[PDB]
Image: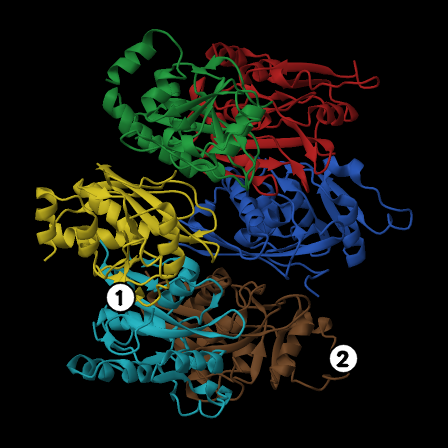
Chain colours: A yellow, B cyan, C brown, D blue, E red, F green
Amino acid sequence: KLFITEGYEVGRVNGLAVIGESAGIVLPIIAEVTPSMEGRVIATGRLQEIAREAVMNVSAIIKKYTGRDISNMDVHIQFVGTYEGVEGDSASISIATAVISAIEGIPVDQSVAMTGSLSVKGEVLPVGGVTQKIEAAIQAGLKKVIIPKDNIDDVLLDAEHEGKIEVIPVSRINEVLEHVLEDGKKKNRLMSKFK
Amino acid sequence: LFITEGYEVGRVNGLAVIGESAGIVLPIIAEVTPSMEGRVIATGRLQEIAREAVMNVSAIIKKYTGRDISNMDVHIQFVGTYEGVEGDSASISIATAVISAIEGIPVDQSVAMTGSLSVKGEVLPVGGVTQKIEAAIQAGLKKVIIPKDNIDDVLLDAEHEGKIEVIPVSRINEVLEHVLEDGKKKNRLMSKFK
Amino acid sequence: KLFITEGYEVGRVNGLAVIGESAGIVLPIIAEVTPSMEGRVIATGRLQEIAREAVMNVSAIIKKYTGRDISNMDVHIQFVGTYEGVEGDSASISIATAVISAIEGIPVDQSVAMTGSLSVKGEVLPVGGVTQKIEAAIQAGLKKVIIPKDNIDDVLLDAEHEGKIEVIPVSRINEVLEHVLEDGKKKNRLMSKFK
Amino acid sequence: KLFITEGYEVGRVNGLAVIGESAGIVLPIIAEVTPSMEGRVIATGRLQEIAREAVMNVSAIIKKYTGRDISNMDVHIQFVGTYEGVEGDSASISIATAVISAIEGIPVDQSVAMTGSLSVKGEVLPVGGVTQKIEAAIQAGLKKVIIPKDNIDDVLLDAEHEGKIEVIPVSRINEVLEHVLEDGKKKNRLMSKFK
Amino acid sequence: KLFITEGYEVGRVNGLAVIGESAGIVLPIIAEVTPSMEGRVIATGRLQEIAREAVMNVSAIIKKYTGRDISNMDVHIQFVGTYEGVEGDSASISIATAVISAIEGIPVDQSVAMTGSLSVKGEVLPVGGVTQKIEAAIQAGLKKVIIPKDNIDDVLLDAEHEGKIEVIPVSRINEVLEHVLEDGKKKNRLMSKFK
Amino acid sequence: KLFITEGYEVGRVNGLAVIGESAGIVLPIIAEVTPSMEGRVIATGRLQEIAREAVMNVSAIIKKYTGRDISNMDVHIQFVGTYEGVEGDSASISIATAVISAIEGIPVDQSVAMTGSLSVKGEVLPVGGVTQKIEAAIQAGLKKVIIPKDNIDDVLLDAEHEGKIEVIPVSRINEVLEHVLEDGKKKNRLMSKFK
């Protein structure tokens, strides 16, 4: 398929969107960074402007917490697939998330499904389409969908579906990163910068 | 999706109509970082109600108060996705929300508002008022600001008149007045409205 | 209504337009303006370049008759109401009167509507659609439609509106300003700056 | 009406176009000129490219013959009227024609329809649309029309419908100003630059 | 008549194309160069974008076998006349033949029409419509027609319509020039440079 | 055909696309490279962004395992023919391979078609409409097809379409190159710098 489901990979993140206004889907991302000689964010398809904003809110938080300054990196983003009549989430957390991973080159867990919106202070803001999605992800066989926690009440799940996925709510990006980044030294050191 | 209690900087419950008649509470966040030439950033279905509305109160963001816009980037979102949402234009809410973010004076969440702002800062009337309010009563918003010329337009089916305080306004500072957190920072904004 | 009808307002003018088939709107413009904290005409939406235009050519009748410089002011020009399929007039003058207003703070006759094209060397040129326009204007319910001279012979009012509106005919930018700058000292001091 | 059919006039030509599939009509031009500060060309409505193809091609000629550099002017052109589904001709000669006039401030016979395309080299070129353009024109009361002479064979016109218009051919531009521009000491000076 | 069927000029070539549904026609271009004083390409009408992308290609080659860089220069492209429902050919060679011609002012034979897409590598790819095309050609009194080497089988030249016209099929632009540029000392140096 | 389906040729490669809903096309790419005479991508239409992107990423890679740098060449990337409503994959390899071609001037198996998306560290990521695409490369007779490996299990190739074409599961641009490059001396000086 268009997504991986088990494993950690750098700078690759399983996001979620809505196709039609009925079913949902995994919107898999990849982000890659190389040096410049000041930088653009390179992304095509119909979701390009969501790439662009996403990085734009994430850049800030990069400098604001690590001093790393990505006007010096060209940022490369592809929606692994192609996505007609798909609607993303404004400033998709999953996009900001892959870039944090790439830039830091700390691997990301793919068993772990994701969607929500994000902001320039670092808050995870609520998004349309939660159930479709939780539900899409139940379908992809992803183990835990992480979601914005204001949507705790928008989740509507048949007792029995409650059961198949670990729905984990959150509301700052530093918690997304703690629930996705691979364990290790690099991670430990990164987390504490978000204090 | 919208918060109905509390205050947050840069963060306003506008009201709009979902196609036919059906008001939606339609929330925003605005933020501002300075620029390293100044832009407006925003996305989804309503990106251009966003850029017209900021670019259209630009004069007024500077020409009463503090900083020129073409010196910050203005990051706007609508919190959720809004297919078939007809929004207002020169949205008092997008303006309120930017002002709020710039001065970091927080905004009242229990109080929805709808209106069109103008470049001299009137609050011109808009349509859908009764629909929008109903959305607001339905959502448990406590008060709602509307334009003064839409006063006549409000036909609430008894029981409903009494579920919501309907506040009519004219000028953008009546709007801010009525939604900003009381404090030094406002006493002070308020008076720069001469 | 989304338009006023009694009042003398500053930065404002009821220019007329044509949407859809033969149809009429009244399209209200609002001017508003700032010594520039070079200058700029900041405007929006479909008829932004019309505005730019109407101001550029109105800039010039002020720089040379009135001794002035628009170069030093951020000219805000907006439109009023949402109209798909709408159509401007080259240099449309409901604008330039709206504007000549901003800068002289001259108050305006919100009972006079108007259409028409403004040349640089000052003249009320003619615009097509002169009949239907007089009518979104009779519903508009307005006591005067100022038109260009050359356009008189396109006025075909039916039985239900002949004698329904004061169609005032005008040729220089000044019989526009004459029949719609509210009375007093500041008009008189300008009217003699032109005449 | 939206054009003048007699007397002369700085910077107005009565050009010609077709409307949807077939009617001839008249495409009135005003072009006017003002001091800059390196300049631009101002046109709004459907026919804006034509006008600026029109002028940028009319300068090299302004120089090579008269040394005005249109570089230091700001040219302002509008079509007098409202023009939907009307197709101009490429670098419409009427339009380069209104500009020589304004810039040279020598007036123009409005009794003479005209049409064709202007090569940057100063060639008058052949154009689609004669017979109906000459009708729109025989309908209008315009006494003569200059056509590119290459379209001489493309003029069908009827027994009763000849007699009523002077079709005149041209190949170069120095011949349109010759054939349209008011006579006067100004005119003779300029005719002499084109050698 | 929109074209010349005989004789030679500079920046003027007779392409070939089709009218909407089925039909074929002669499509006179003309392309002039003045220094850019960066080089924009310029042209208006329905063919306007078949003009820029055709030109923006060609110069791989325009730079590459021969004379000048065209970012230094300005391109004015007109289709002589007006072109309601006509599909032109991608990277048109009659455009390329024209721009090359206009840059070295080396006149083109107009008794020869050509059609075909120029690769950027300067090969001629095949183009549809060919049979139709050769025929507008024949209708039109032109003497020889260059076509693409691969639209050969596609030449369904009937009874009537054989021997009336010479078909010169070709595979390179450099061939296109050979067959149509004016025998002269400049051309001999042009041809050796496409060695 | 406008389509090479056998041979070996420099800068020419066979892309696939799903035009519209399921409809597959074969969409051939032409690369051409010019010693920038800093340097810049040159393409046209709906897919210029893709080509520029596919060139971006390709570069990171050539700059690496080959050590030659392609900011000193201008880059001409054509697509062959007119189809409409299309959706090229992000970083499409059809392109990236065409380049390394234009650049290593190493001609290419024209029997193979491919679809894919290129990462910057060069991984071949999978794209969408993988089935419909095999089906148009088939229906165009290309003796083989390259495809993203992660897309192997979405190949809904039936019992009708089972034994018609070499389907190639591929994980990285070098295997892509191993498999379409022409057996000889620079290829091997290539593939060997790619270890």
| CB within 8 Å, label 2 to label 1 | no
What residue do we see at 60% from left, 24% from top? E116
Q: Under tag 1, what secondary structure?
A: loop
Q: CA gap, disc 2 to disc 1?
A: 52 Å
Q: Position of residue E195 (x, y in %)?
A: 47, 9
Residue E14 placement (x, y as % from top left): 65, 27
Tag on residue C158?
2
Name above or below for residue E56 compared with residue A5. Answer: above
Horizontally, residue B143 falls left or right of residue E89, namely left
Q: Is residue D99 above or below residue C143?
A: above
Identify the secondary structure beneath mark 2: loop
Is B183 placed left or right of A77 in the picture? Answer: left
Residue F130 at least partly seen? yes
Q: Chain of mark 1?
A: B
Name the residue carrying label 1.
Answer: B68
Seen as rendered, the residue at the extreme right is D159
Pick whichever, A101 or D159, lies toward us: A101
What x and y, as percent, mark residue B21?
Answer: 52, 75
Could you say where residue F8 lies in the image, as x and y percent from the top left?
Answer: 47, 13
| Rendered position, C100 above or below D92 | below
**Callout 2: chain:** C
Q: Amino acid at mark 2?
A: Asp
Q: Which mark is residue C99?
A: none
Q: Toward which corner of the image does residue B164 lie, by quadrant?
A: bottom left
Q: Quadrant of residue F37?
A: top left
Q: Which quadrant is home to the N terminus of chain D? A: bottom right
Question: Can residue D193 be seen?
Answer: no
Foreground of the two, A64 or E178: A64
| C34 up-or-down from A160: above or below | below
Amino acid at the residue labelled 1 = Asp
Please state, as top left, top right, bottom left or bottom right, where the C terminus of chain D lies in the image: top right
